[PDB]
Amino acid sequence: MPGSGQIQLWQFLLELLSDSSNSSCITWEGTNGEFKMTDPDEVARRWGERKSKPNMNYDKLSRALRYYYDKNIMTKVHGKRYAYKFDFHGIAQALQPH
Amino acid sequence: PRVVPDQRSKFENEEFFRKLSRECEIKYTGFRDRPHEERQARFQNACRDGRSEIAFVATGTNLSLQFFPPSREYVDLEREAGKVYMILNGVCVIWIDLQRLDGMGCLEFDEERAQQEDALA
Amino acid sequence: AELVRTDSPNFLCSVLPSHWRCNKTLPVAFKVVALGEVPDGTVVTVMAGNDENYSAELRNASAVMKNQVARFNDLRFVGRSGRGKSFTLTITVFTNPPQVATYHRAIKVTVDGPREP
DNA sequence: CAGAGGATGTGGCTTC
DNA sequence: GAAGCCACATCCTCTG
Ligand SMILES: [Mg+2]
């Protein structure tokens, strides 16, 4: 599926969760699927670096993530300043049929 | 006017009508974004009321039907098990599986109403 | 507004543009005209017909006849027609009995409204 | 102000 | 290769 060839967000984002060196800008939160957002504007700044989009900020990146909701890719941790979580149980139905 | 003057001519001339004169591939168009279980209940509950939304898949032509002037000859669920048996473009004209929500139908020129309607002029 | 022919010469509708984006506020809201006297209150629904996805998803698809003219607040085309292909959309008029006017080569529904390529 | 979300242009990418 | 897709880009909008 075209997640392999062309770079996504959730694909790109998790380059940084699993990588211990980039814990400066993000980290997993607990056993269950959850993640923090350390430097919200730096997070974006690198997403801009990759997307060749220097203008990029959080507000821009963020929206794209708020699409994911309706698609069942990830969801929000309600109230928590910059904390969402992945719907893997869905990613596979979204990467394979049933 | 409600109908065209040459009511019989149009049905037996127009490409549109003769394409739907033969028994063609039809399917239920109602509630496309709903699960297979719900669609089966809605379609059947509608047929009994005397209405539905069927389209000729081959051509694309969609329709909303009314089986009326409850009814006997218009909607019949007894003819076979697991299935059931207007003025189009100014021309008076007249089965689906209860599990698959697909089957076969067609148009037929209404000689009865084409005289009744043309008389109103 | 500007009108166009139908397959029923008893009813006429808006000039829905050539090619438009998947679910967009239409550039000119949909006007359906009744030349034969229709009771101002009768409902008028539409169904997008095409060999591909025979019944596409539509929004604000139902409207109310008023002063012999049914206006669709803002109809929107969700289900795409495909490459080159366009909808032969069906136009119902809930009466006893109902009447329809088919409309071939109505509009081309893609994910892009035609850009400068 | 973050957070959900309608609108609408954008650019890389498969498909005729 | 224009013609359909695609998955964000940019945008301004409300409201808790
Ligand atoms: Mg707006």
Image (tube, coloured by chain):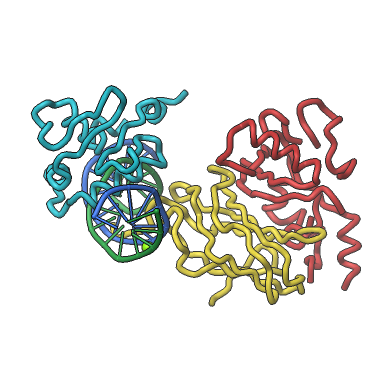
Chain colours: A cyan, B red, C yellow, D blue, E green
Q: Is residue C34 left or right of residue B5?
A: left
Residue for point 69% across, 46% down:
B53
Residue for point 76% across, 36% down:
B95
Q: Quadrant of the C terminus of chain C?
A: bottom left
- Tell me if residue A8 comes above or below residue A92 in the rendering: below
The one nearer the camera, E14 or E2, is: E14
Q: Is residue C99 left or right of residue C3?
A: right
Residue for point 15% across, 54% down:
A55
Q: Position of residue C78 (x, y in %)?
A: 49, 51
- Tell me if residue B70 comes above or below residue C88 in the rendering: above
Among the 4 quarters of the image, the one containing residue A91: top left
Residue for point 11% across, 32% down:
A22
**Res. A51 in view:** no
- The quarter of the image that holds ligand 1 is bottom left
- Tell me if residue B41 comes above or below residue B16 in the rendering: above
Among the 4 quarters of the image, the one containing residue B48: top right
Among the 4 quarters of the image, the one containing residue B70: top right
Q: How many marks?
A: 0
Q: Position of residue C70 (x, y in %)?
A: 64, 69
Q: Quadrant of the N terminus of chain C?
A: bottom right
Q: Is residue B51 left or right of residue E2?
A: right
The one nearer the camera, B105 or E15, is: E15
Q: Position of residue B51 (x, y in %)?
A: 76, 47
**Res. C96 in view:** yes
Q: Position of residue C32 (x, y in %)?
A: 63, 68
